[PDB]
Image (tube, rainbow over all chains, first blue to last red; front, side, top):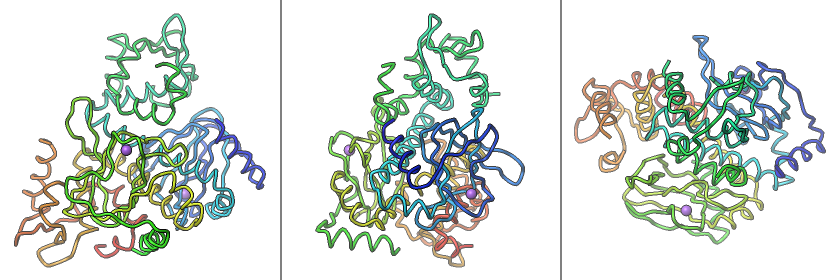
Length: 229
Length: 228
Ligand code: NA
Ligand code: NA
């Protein structure tokens, strides 16, 4: 991606260097009083919220290049008590104290717009997920997740559309009611788990039950959306 | 609010002037190729979608002051096939062509930050609502909505936290939804008295909508403190 690469080298030229994180590490955490701007360049991360009960809530999954800010750009206070856990085996992210981000994005506004557009895509993505859910429930929720993963990491094989993402990661992404829906998916042969990898064989089904998230990926990632459309 | 007033003065000084809209009108729609940046200064609105079935879908609600954009700021293309419909009797909004907004923000970064943090507030609201769902179902969803309405338009009287809103607008604010709302009413969480609504068990709402309560504290503590 062009905007992401230009933003990376903008950060690097201003003295901000990348940082490596192995799986299960938190790039930021809900107890740190200092907020940051994570520019997740490479790897797969997970936004979590740990309540006092020790219970972990998976709120969102990000994949570089993306931007995740734990604090408000103006007040610098927490936008929510969240952690960013690396779920891939290793990830590369740029960590920028919320205050320095203002200085850096105020001089060069071209990448200011990049951060802006990432936030906008988050908004539209959440609204599309809410719509798909509110009509087709979790069947559509899981269909939309599988659909976007097929778009990004899917490439064709004699068996279907192989999800090239490593099995370990895909396990980290949850792959009673969820597994029941997934077993029905396997019943109608929409997806097939074979030879250590996932395969999508009926793309139109996932598209049918995730229309709004499909529209979202079309309006937000048209170049990659058209890979299998 | 203050930053909203400053953004208004920035739009005014820069030639952009407001427009008045009426209930059921659309500030923008899902068929217009031109995308805009709406600075909803006053009134209440909802972002809706029309699925292939053809029936309305209420996605989000917005109070002024706030910002709602139909297209991305870089490509100027749609972020989604949505319509902004006024549910208040009157609404005052500034409709800025998206292309112009880029230059306008680039000239002053303070108002850029205002719009950016509005987006951040949206993001955090969506995440907190999803968490409240994962925890307590639609019950917590509607409890969070009632909680936000209580904080915003809540004036405390002995009959409870009276709701400033005209009940015409609350008519806009479906089986299961009305079923849970009426059960909240029957459990005397929200009573009806003297032609108005009164939240007499705010703690119930706080209990079944904790993540959005935290969100409101972290994003608007000014009004959060009044009822806490
Ligand atoms: Na933090
Ligand atoms: Na539009």
